[PDB]
Image (cartoon, rainbow, N blue to C red; front, side, top):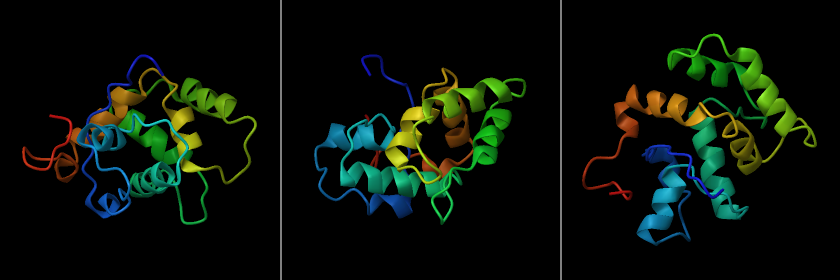
Length: 138
């Protein structure tokens, strides 16, 4: 990506333990903002954990389209379900029933409204907003 997604910084405490080798402040900021794209074991681990906390990924590794659509609806986008699922499905067309978390991220972020949707989800999860001390993106 050359244009950033504009996702806000997520502070999901049970997934902080997946940030092991990344130590640079801004690099960790991009992790928490789900702006990472590189297929590394570390990024995979963290994004997998986040998507588990999002309810987007179950214990068997299947994507949960109902959780995604719920977030769209809760962000006020109720008349877009077809476009959202077709964007995801087309993007995932070469992948099987248990895809890796970085590829799921790449596909869910193609819809232009996904950053707004997930930003509204963070707004209603105050525990997921880092305070002044813990934030990396400031």
